[PDB]
Amino acid sequence: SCAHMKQQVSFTGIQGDSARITCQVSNAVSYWIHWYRFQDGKPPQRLLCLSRESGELLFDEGFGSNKFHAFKDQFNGEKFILLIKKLEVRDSGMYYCAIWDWDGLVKVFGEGTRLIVTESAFKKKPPKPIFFLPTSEEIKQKQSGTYICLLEDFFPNVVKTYWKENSQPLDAQFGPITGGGNSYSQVSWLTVKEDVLRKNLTYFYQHEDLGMEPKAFSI
Amino acid sequence: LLESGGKVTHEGQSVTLTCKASGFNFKDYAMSWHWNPSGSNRQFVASISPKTGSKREYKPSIQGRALITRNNEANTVSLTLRQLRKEDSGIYYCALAEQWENFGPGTELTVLPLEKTLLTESGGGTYQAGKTLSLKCQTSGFQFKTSQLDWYLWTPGHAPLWLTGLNSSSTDATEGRITSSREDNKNQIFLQIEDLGLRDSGQYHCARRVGNGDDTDKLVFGLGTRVIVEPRPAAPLSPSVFLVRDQDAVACLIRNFYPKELHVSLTSGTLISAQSLSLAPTASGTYSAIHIGRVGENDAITCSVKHLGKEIHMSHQA
Ligand SMILES: *[C@@H]1O[C@H](CO)[C@@H](O)[C@H](O)[C@H]1NC(C)=O
Image 1 (cartoon, rainbow over the protein chains, first blue to last red):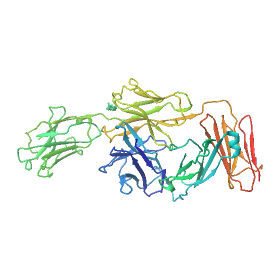
Image 2 (cartoon, rainbow over the protein chains, first blue to last red):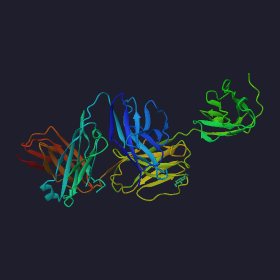
Image 3 (spheres, each protein chain N blue to C red):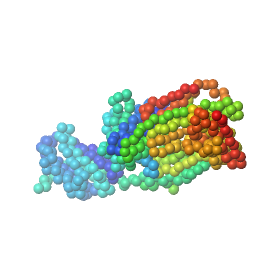
Image 4 (tube, helix red, strand yellow):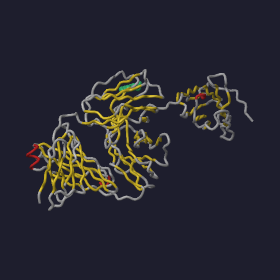
């Protein structure tokens, strides 16, 4: 019964606008949500910390309310927002929400929301999947099948994918995300043995355009 | 004449000293704070007329960072010192320049030198599964033995994760695939990951816990050092090539080949313009790959895979 942090896979906003990075907490009692940033090249630092009870914020060295504000969403309950105001490109990076757990000796972080700041307006296109089933030649030759999913033509260059028949996600191979401009893509293949081939497995994927809940494909 | 405060803090942080009085007209008399560095140098540092702050002369040596305020409802007279310094250590007493000689029993403020947290990780690179990885973290700028030090794993697309840590009265030396040790003499800490797995890849981060000692605390992280895990070097295995077409979109599925220096290309002798290779190792110790492109529902295709030593093609007709 450990504490989990659900964050949107990414947030992109036009430069000069705001950025609501959401974080939904599960099984936390710590009264204090922290916000950490990881900027590629710099050590990761805490921006600030918010009190779940009182609402007071404590900023860290060189951070302040002009650029950051942390609150608790009145809607949906137990949702917490880090609002990064007046976005710049130095503001790009990874934004995590964190808490203390297990009697305060371990700190638990969210999966992370990548903030990407576009120099101008941007098309927020969603990913399109295509699925290749295992062939009769591949089951004859290798006594196993391979489900190949190609997620194509999505923006931004951020996406999470997994497979689950079982509650724990299944171990797949994931390709490098390849693309440029306003189109990126990623392939992921799952080699499943000739026994579990009949089982109805389900393929899950998450992208900024589809919000917080994942999308699923059966068989 | 009973004041409170005077905790122990470091030379960047503020403090608020308070003073409570009973038995006389507190509302009507002036009130001052004095200071003796360790004693015997009681000097007027702050003066206020509790009527209200009409005459407030706190500027001997602490000007700019002293604020005395008198409430009189709880009979409180505070001196807030906002930016303390090494020489602010001393006994703070409660009492044109109005004469003050009815001193009280001053509290003591002890201020400690500044702590900068320099954490430098080292010992990363690329390693083969099963091999034992030892990581170093140089820690400078704080009292080592009574710190709280932890290792964290930052994997892209994964939540950062705590590996192993230690306290002042730790005396633990946890056993397992996660090992943490500390050298007190060299002011160093060490991580050890035997039998490196694949999910064991990412940037490893030394971390110090700083703050008041409560849930308000934060983690100072080092730059970190990166660790890649690559398959246990196995004998050459040659790939099994298959082609899977689907509605003007073909894929070439290649599998079970170490090494993975192959050049896979989709071509009837015509080189495809849209085709990309994705190489990834499996849970067996060898790489698989997929080279994917587009060719219509009528057109026929070929795939070529030049894994060293051999060269395998598979073609599908119209
Ligand atoms: C180390 O962890 C234990 C966990 O119960 C905690 O009680 C202890 O206070 C910690 N060490 C120090 C010096 O605080």
